Each structure stands twice: as structure tokens, then as C-alpha cells.
Amino acid sequence: PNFRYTHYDLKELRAGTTLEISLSSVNNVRLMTGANFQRFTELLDFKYLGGVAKKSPIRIAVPETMHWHLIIDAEGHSGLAESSVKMLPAQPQATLTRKAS
Amino acid sequence: PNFRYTHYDLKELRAGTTLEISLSSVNNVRLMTGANFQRFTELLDFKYLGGVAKKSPIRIAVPETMHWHLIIDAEGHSGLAESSVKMLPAQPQATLTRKAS
Image 1 (tube, chains in turn yellow, cyan):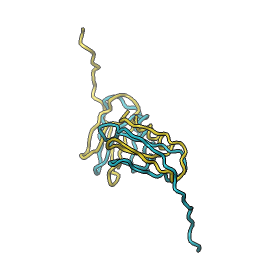
Image 2: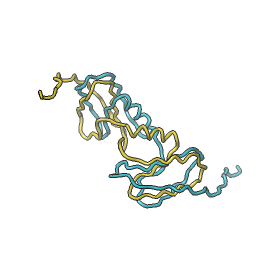
Image 3: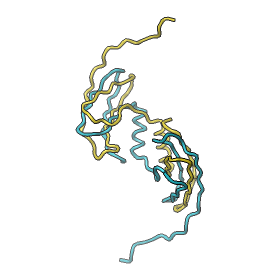
Image 4: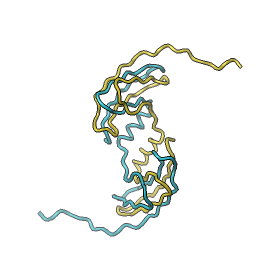
């Protein structure tokens, strides 16, 4: 899991119900609907390679053989970059083993 | 949608395939598997009320009547806070209308 959390299922509450929430240290507090709780549980397992790109072009090597998706996105940024992707052939690689015991 | 993005479905690629990615401005670049692309599409619609809590206790009022979930979490923080939640009754409220035309 990407980080630890505590989940209170508060069930059905009427608009205007006030939650009084106590905490021992700086942490995030998020009140959400059931649909959004389902989204949250998905994002606990969300993994990817990359991050903020400040130079161009960049190269990223695919780590394992499988179906891959590349996202360019403006999360935390003012706008969406124009982008292009060129798929370069893998270098030949040997598969390693352990040393003979 | 929480932010704009561009999605390249690169299909099946062998380990070691190198993606050369060009961008016009600072943006995020994320290479991910199909399962993780499904998670990503969920997080484009992820909405909640709250944020980083620096005082305690805090109060959050439920905005609409429905099934609610409260998350306390350590995303971006060193550790998970101890927490408690007390559910306080809603204040009586009138429903407003428009002024008579």
C-alpha cells in the first residue's frame, strides 16, 4: 500500500451533520462519498514509472514485457504539454543467474 | 476531470524497449501497466472534502445526504496520526427558493 490510513465508514448521514475530528499529528483528513471511497482504494495500489519532466526529450525503458500505457498530464501544472513518443528497439540483453554455489 | 492528460496506448512491449518522449513544457510523464491505467482513470474523477489538518479537533459539515466515509491518512507525511471522530447532530435548516419574479 502506498501509505497508511484509517477508514471510518460513517454510513448514511443527513446534510449538515458535523463531524468533529481529533488527530494526534499533522495528517490528511478526507470526507468522501462511497463512489469516491472506491476510487480511493484503487489509488492505494496505483503505481507508475516517471514523474515531473523538466527536460526534453527524456528516455524511459520499459522494465518488464507487458501491455504499457504512457500518460502525459498536467496534474499540479498550469496546462497540458504538447508531446510525442518514439518507440526505440530494446538492446539485446542476457538473462543473469546466481553464481555457482 | 481533475486535470488534462494525453494517453498513448503502447500495447505490448518487450522489456528494454525505450520510449523517447518529447514535451513542450513542464508536465508529468508516467509509464504504467494496464491495471494501473485503470486506477489512473478512476483518479481523474476522485473528489473529496478536506485536506491537510494542522489543528485539532477540526469540524467538517456533510454537504448532502448520502453514505459518507472519513479517511485519515499519511499521504506525504512521515506516519499515521491517531484519530477519533464524533458525529454531531445537524442544525435545523430551511430550504431556500428564488425570489418571486
